[PDB]
Image (cartoon, rainbow, N blue to C red):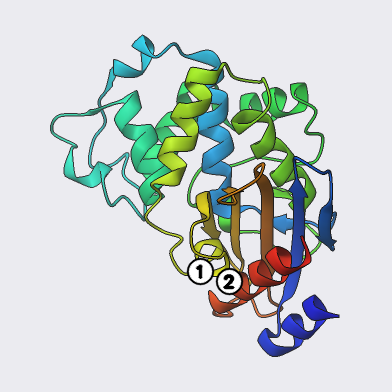
Amino acid sequence: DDFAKLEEQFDAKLGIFALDTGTNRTVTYRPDERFAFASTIKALTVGVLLQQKSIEDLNQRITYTRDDLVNYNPITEKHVDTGMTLKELADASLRYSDNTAQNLILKQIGGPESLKKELRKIGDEVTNPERFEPELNEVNPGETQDTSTARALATSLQAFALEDKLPSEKRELLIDWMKRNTTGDALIRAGVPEGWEVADKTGAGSYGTRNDIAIIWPPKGDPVVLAVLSSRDKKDAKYDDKLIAEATKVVVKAL
């Protein structure tokens, strides 16, 4: 079918789960196969952070040093000498995919184990967070550490952004940051028709892993929850964003 043809054109494996929350119609393809979640986990991490912290708590200033910095710190590496509030760290993790911001947030909620417990509480029995950034991207075939599935990632995102795991105000908070993400212009955003609103979180890992999860709103209709995951067989393989955009067109077309 259309998705298998894409796996052939891009020589990659596709993980897809899409749910029209207004009709319960879905689009799936290897919906339950595991993939390294990479940075998409940052969205669920802030979801759990919003569960534990009040809006007032987010103003708490977090200080750190040049050594706390990891490999990809676009925003945090510019505020070492002044620190950043939790709200600012959440903005940089979600919108710029800042790795240090995610680590500081993760530390705030109790580490990867606490994140797992909380996801287990909301019904997510698949996602398996174990490490910090950027080590969590080091996932080899057959391993479940730091992996999840399209269905589980989409469902958990749905839980925090559309359900009731968070009160409306915090919901809107999460959605607005994601709506203003800066890293997914060539992914899900490039596969939906004009007029469609997208709130997404991207990811990239070893084995050419390239993912994007989002909540997309048609100009007319209820929101669609979508997770498009992918990986390749070479550990050092390069990914092509076009695969995600195309897969998204197929999903929009089918729905």
Which of the image's four quarters has the N terminus? Answer: bottom right
| Whole-percent x, y for residue 65 in the image | 23, 35
Q: Earlier in the sequence, mark 1 or mark 2?
A: 1
Question: Seen in the image, is 51 located left or right of residue 8?
Answer: left
| Whole-percent x, y for residue 205 in the image | 57, 63
Amino acid at pointer 2? Ala
Q: Nearer the viewer, residue 56 or 253?
A: 253
Which residue is rendered at x = 60% and y = 61% of the image? Answer: 211
Is residue 149 visible in the rendered image? The answer is: no
Which residue is rendered at x = 54% and y = 40% of the image? Answer: 43
Q: Is residue 234 above or below residue 34?
A: below
Q: Which residue is mark 1?
A: 190
The number of numbered discs placed on residues in the rendered structure image is 2
Which of the image's four quarters has the C terminus? Answer: bottom right
Picture quadrant of residue 118: top right
The reply to whether dot 1 and dot 2 touch (C-beta < 8 Å) is yes
Q: Is residue 7 above or below residue 205?
A: below
Q: Which residue is mark 2?
A: 245
- Crowding around mark 2 (Cα neighbors within 10 Å: few <14, some 14 to 19, many 20+) is many
Q: Secondary structure at mark 1?
A: helix
Q: Is residue 218 above or below residue 45?
A: below
| Whole-percent x, y for residue 77 in the image | 23, 46
Q: Secondary structure at mark 2?
A: helix
Which residue is rendered at x = 71% and y = 24% of the image? Answer: 117
Amino acid at pointer 1? Ala
- Crowding around mark 1 (Cα neighbors within 10 Å: few <14, some 14 to 19, many 20+) is some
Which residue is rendered at x = 61% and y = 70% of the image? Answer: 244
Q: Nearer the viewer, residue 124 or 185?
A: 185
Picture quadrant of residue 27: bottom right
Question: Seen in the image, is 5 located left or right of residue 214?
Answer: right
Toward the left, the furthest residue is 81
Q: Is residue 196 above or below residue 131?
A: below
